[PDB]
Length: 224
Image (cartoon, rainbow, N blue to C red; front, side, top):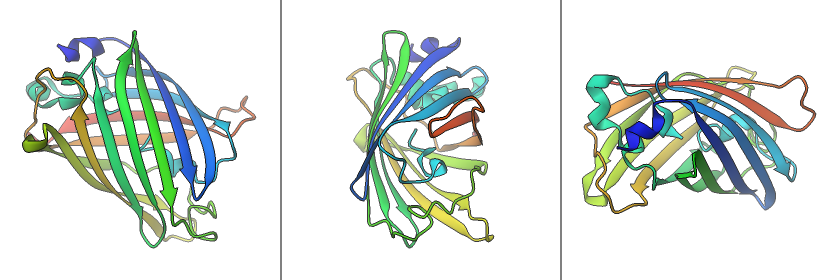
């Protein structure tokens, strides 16, 4: 029945507790998701510390329950089926020839609000590398995310490689290893293999003085 929680517009709260090479920071995100259109609109603000990594590196970490699953694919929507109790999302993100993020999040309803509570630890970042040196372009490429069931672990596994464009025409690769597991004991949908097509647009609020990121996404499930 978790699918039914997502028929209209759902308010979203994101809270990120970050520590990258000892540099501590917090980010708060507010907006809303409309899974009917696979649409996310969020504004993220740095609320503690100085931002020691580029905004684009945090996009994947900062709620796939807002994906649009076409009607013929509804039986493959693990993310909504885990709600409202929610799921744990864990990743390791390897930045090629640089450091790594380890993330743990709980995605669940808290009253009527979909909440993404994240802990992020970054280590091994190079001082004059693409991340700590803020050399990534403020943009995002369209990416496909390949979803597989891991039935023996009662969840899903997701591998994918983000390409972050750099001005000089090189790219910073970010290799993602993701697992999602239900929080609840209730039955969830374990999907057939499929992907999510994710389009992301990054912008700025011209009225906002704090370090921030405005994000618009469209996410569509395909490939069954």
